[PDB]
Image (cartoon, helix red, strand yellow):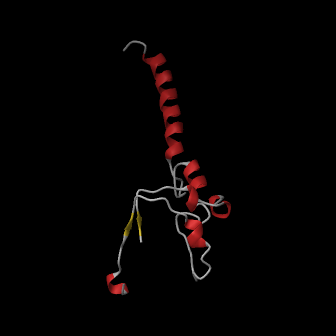
Amino acid sequence: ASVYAWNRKRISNCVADYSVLYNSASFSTFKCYGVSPTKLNDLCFTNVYA
Amino acid sequence: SALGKLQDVVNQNAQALNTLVKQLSSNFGAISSVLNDILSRLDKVEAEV
């Protein structure tokens, strides 16, 4: 999406592995603001919004 | 109502303990009131702050 009209896909009803994402070294940034990226695999959530 | 002096001494301790317990819920400017949630969500270098 163009940033004037950003998309917001709901992610729900799944098992995730954020280490797969974090290990994608092609990502130029992975800053986290209320959780640590190492801890994500121990957590669970009601929803994630992409 | 006659035993006010004794009941007051019990009531003061009840208010003091209930305040001391309620204060565990106060954030004190941390991101959460619950120590185990900080330790679940955050890694040492941030969690120590």
Quadrant in the picture for residue B2: top left
Residue in front for this viewpoint, B7 or B29: B29
User: Horizontal and vertical percent for residue B10?
Assistant: 49, 22
User: Horizontal and vertical percent for residue B49?
Assistant: 63, 60
The quadrant the N terminus of chain A occupies is: bottom left
The quadrant the C terminus of chain A occupies is: bottom left
Outermost residue toward the left in this view = A5
Outermost residue toward the top in this view = B2
User: Horizontal and vertical percent for residue A28?
Assistant: 58, 83
Residue beneath the point at 62% across and 73% down: A23
Instruction: State whether residue A2 is above or below residue B42.
Output: below
Quadrant in the picture for residue A10: bottom left
Instruction: State whether residue A28 is above or below residue B2.
Output: below
Instruction: State whether residue B28 is above or below residue B4.
Output: below
Residue beneath the point at 53% across and 56% down: A43
Q: How many marks?
A: 0
Instruction: State whether residue B44 is above or below residue B15.
Output: below
Quadrant in the picture for residue B1: top left
User: Horizontal and vertical percent for residue A9?
Assistant: 36, 71
Residue beneath the point at 46% across and 22% down: B8
